[PDB]
Amino acid sequence: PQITLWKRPLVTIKIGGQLKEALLDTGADDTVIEEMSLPGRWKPKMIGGIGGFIKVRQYDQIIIEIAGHKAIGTVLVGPTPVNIIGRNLLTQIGATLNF
Amino acid sequence: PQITLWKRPLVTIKIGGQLKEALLDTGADDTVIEEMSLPGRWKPKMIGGIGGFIKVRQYDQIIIEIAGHKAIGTVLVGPTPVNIIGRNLLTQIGATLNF
Ligand SMILES: CC(C)CN(C[C@@H](O)[C@H](Cc1ccccc1)NC(=O)O[C@H]1CO[C@H]2OCC(F)(F)[C@H]21)S(=O)(=O)c1ccc(N)cc1
Ligand SMILES: [Cl-]
Ligand SMILES: [Cl-]
Ligand SMILES: [Cl-]
Ligand code: NA
Image (cartoon, rainbow over the protein chains, first blue to last red):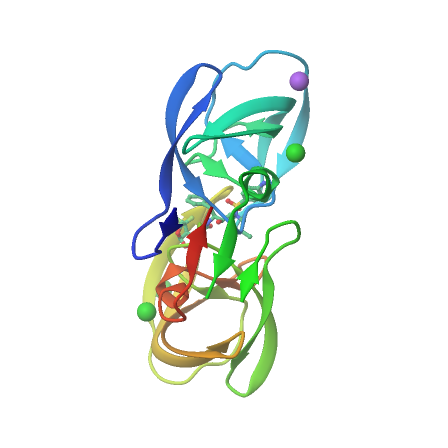
């Protein structure tokens, strides 16, 4: 689709068997999701933000479905105020900014 | 143009006759730029992200060029880690997300 930016670009995702709403965020290098369980190994990470950092768990090789499109990549899990789909997974669904 | 997301979507902006680099950020409601001098009065605003909130100065009806496209609108100034072009000005330059 073509998504205008008059409102937040929110979409439905499927991750870990769960449906969630997430923000398509070209200003995010990586994907960050609110606390949930995911399978496999993880390692700690700090991720930056406009106001400072939060501690997250880094899970690699996680499959997500993003508005109907399957991707695989790293997902960070931690106390983000909103679920955000970052560039690491936006590239995989072929998302571009056009003007 | 059509901007892919394998790297950060950084463009040149021009504000107060100065060139700066800024990130095109669909996850930002608001344009926020690092400390600089802007004309006129400002109003207070609170904006929040990963790591919490920052206090910013809101300047309205500021002339800003973004990747060669003219915009005139609200610019927030504060301790953001990078200059961010948010949806309030992305809509003025006709940007959409596409996949
Ligand atoms: C700051 C920017 C360089 C990076 N961020 C992504 C942003 O898109 C962020 C994404 C974001 C969205 C919503 C809440 C938290 C973060 N938006 C944001 O801070 O926008 C602020 C300016 O306008 C307001 O609108 C949303 C806001 F946050 F409120 C304010 S981020 O959230 O800090 C971030 C950093 C690293 C990773 N991997 C993922 C995300
Ligand atoms: Cl990845
Ligand atoms: Cl104040
Ligand atoms: Cl505006
Ligand atoms: Na894994």
